Length: 129
Ligand SMILES: Cc1cn([C@H]2C[C@H](OP(=O)(O)O)[C@@H](COP(=O)(O)O)O2)c(=O)[nH]c1=O
Ligand SMILES: [Ca+2]
Image (cartoon, rainbow, N blue to C red; front, side, top):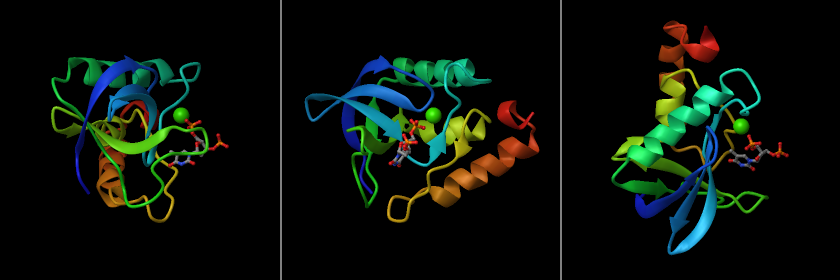
């Protein structure tokens, strides 16, 4: 896979963000994770966590996987990086998202994220508390 540039337009929630990519505004849905909706338990904390990670970053990147690059809603499907740290993994490692939505062909970072989830679960963090 390859990191590509993007710039933040706006935080949305724990697993969606509005970024400018190839010069066009797009909503991105983070691959392989599910954060609680804002109205759910830990939804606010997941939103805040992503918000802070993307707003503080000097360099935002997106990395598409091998399969579908946009979902049925027109959302881009990517791994997002903030100053070289993957937001998808960071959310899981902190117990603020579950590994989820693992479709064949867009699952390159599956095992990295499951390893993170195991550790968040061991530590009883957030969702796992
Ligand atoms: C993460 C992801 C979600 N989606 C679709 C599946 C779900 O369909 P439904 O809307 O029919 O439930 C929805 C979940 O996204 P959200 O968790 O943002 O709601 O997005 C994909 O198609 N591919 C993906 O890789
Ligand atoms: Ca969600």
